[PDB]
Image (cartoon, rainbow, N blue to C red):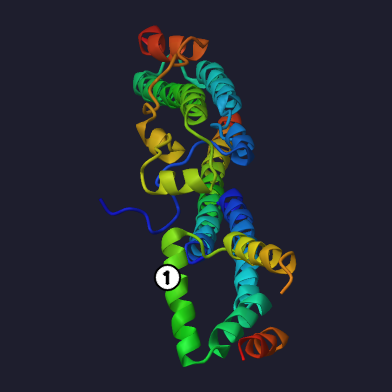
Amino acid sequence: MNDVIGFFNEREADLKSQYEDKKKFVKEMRDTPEFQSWMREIRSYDQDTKEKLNKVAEKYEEEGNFNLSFVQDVLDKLESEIAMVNHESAVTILDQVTA
Amino acid sequence: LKDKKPFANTKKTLENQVEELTEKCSLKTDEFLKAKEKINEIFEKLNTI
Amino acid sequence: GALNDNPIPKSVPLHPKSGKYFHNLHARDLSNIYQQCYKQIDETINQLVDSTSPSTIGIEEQVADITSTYKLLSTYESESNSFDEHIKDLKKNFKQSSDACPQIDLSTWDKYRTGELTAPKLSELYLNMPTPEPATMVNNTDTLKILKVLPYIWN
């Protein structure tokens, strides 16, 4: 029984170490600063904006698109199409032309 | 750990069993030694003969 | 079955710490006491010859009673001898069976306490140990020869 109690104490020291470490990890995750920032951004949208973003969230996650990879790739694609294709003078000169 | 609590309790029980059985062995040894003493007294009586 | 919520197992194999304790487990050598007895009885025989008046009869009952006494004493010695032999054989068998049984850890603690693992129990085996019998009754001393023949020699 002496040996048995020693072994039990060792095994439960290991289990307590693991459980405490992961409980601390969860406490870090509850609430993680990234988690808090993402929640703040999510709740920062207005009514219609948050509704539309939630609908697009459903769309992307149905496609699996809702990830940093796809979102960032779309960002970079639009950035490449905008910066390379450099964009009242036109409208006013057109009006002068027409008159 | 809840299990370990009964482990400690019945470990104390085991130690008590050890102590009691050792004491019983000692007492039976004492009684047997007293029987031996009686046998030695009878030895001495025989020499008187 | 009522499992052991009492973690003390019903039976456990030989723990080495008590393996040492088990080495000290033995019947005490009482043969010295028996030799003292046998010497005293031989002296009793010699003095019984020395004192008893050859003209007086009535020693047959003395010799018969001491004959029965010495047979009883030799029987006791033999019982102790067979007890020691049974202790030796029991110890050998218990060690072999216990070592054949898994040693004790927390897992085997639960198995042994719940009856999943069963090992020889020296208390149980000692109960199952053969009862001390007269093993080589010490009758070969000159003591029983005279205690047997002396009634007739007195006649």
The picture places residue C103, in percent across and down from the top left corner, at 53, 37
The picture places residue C141, in percent across and down from the top left corner, at 51, 11
**Depth check, front residue: C120 or C151:** C120
Q: Is residue A53 above or below residue A48?
A: above
The picture places residue B19, in percent across and down from the top left corner, at 56, 56
Q: Residue visible at 61% across and 26% down?
A: C32
**Depth check, front residue: B27 or A85:** A85
- Quadrant for residue C128, please give it: top left
**Depth check, front residue: C78 or A97:** A97
Give the residue number, with chain letter if any, for mark 1. A58
Q: Residue visible at 64% across and 69% down?
A: A25
The picture places residue B36, in percent across and down from the top left corner, at 55, 38
Q: Is residue A7 above or below residue C145?
A: below
- Quadrant for residue A62, please give it: bottom left
In the image as oriented, which residue stretches furthest toward the left? C1
Badge 1: how crowded within 10 Å, few (<14), some, or many (20+)?
A: some
Q: Residue visible at 60% across and 54% down?
A: A11
Could you tell me which secondary element the residue under label 1 belongs to?
Answer: helix
Give the quadrant of the C terminus of chain C.
Answer: top left
Q: Amino acid at mark 1?
A: Glu
